[PDB]
Image 1 (cartoon, rainbow, N blue to C red):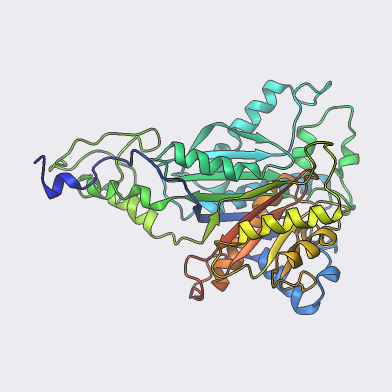
Image 2: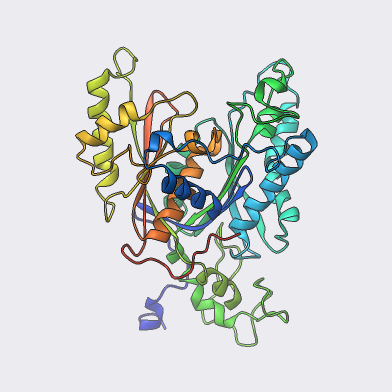
Length: 431
């Protein structure tokens, strides 16, 4: 009835969204060279246990050729297994039978480049099918992938994806979750390359590790606003339970129909079964990802990089803005300047001016992604988010991630625990 308490409750998806200041990290999957999932974070903490100074921790990548692939056929096979494992790790416990809106992230690719190894049509098709196709080797037979419009990202520095996701969630108030699959390694650099670039110069082929080669890195990152499914809890009791009870797919209403007509939305095309909401609710929020802060590092009049002291002040201001809303203040910094970089030359004065208590010389507070993991290329900001999520979830504390590979810009992404001060009983980052 029209003016009733029951008509007050929502039987439709939210029609508006406020400005969003966080997204929830719902799931992480990661492969990084021979490591998987929490093994990367474990290896970093073991570095800190043996070496107190961040400057001397070195790289976790095994150098014993017996412990990593060296033949070209083994490297190709390992790359593909790393891809599948990362998707499996990120999705195995995530809602099935719902089209997951998906962003695919790889490194930069210029389609006008002469003599490409693959045609632009071949490459665009390859990128478009990549994540859905990985469901087969990953064993994700009931999961569903819905490529987002303009969701194929080719960018050496793709950290802008996170701010773009905030806007996407605001523009689409029904959207409850998005998958970002970031995919990096020699195999990508090679498949995007021109025949005028020899593959060996990118570190490909048979042989031991050479310096500068991209680390095989894949990150499955699911972020969302889980409250946005609450309106579906109205309809779930009326949905028919599948004969195979653990199958979440909606296959119609039961005998009793819901009191209000269900109206699908772009991202909620069908009502959700009780099994679906069970899968949704069983996945704990791992962290809050806070709205990124980006700041230019160049002068607008000359276009040159800010001078030493102006750069410190600019970065300090960005840190203050990015860290203000973190409870408590960051316990560690993950940052990445890429290869042949010394980012502490700028970071130490900047965080000092910002009066941060972090000691970036302390290996327990200070993580240079390229130093410790090799060059993770386009996956780097998602590696940072993944490790920050693991650290913050397991420790009930805050982290900061700083993509610093652009010389003209700094980005700062805060990561907080949803229950700070409380560590979880179960570590969910096993393999």
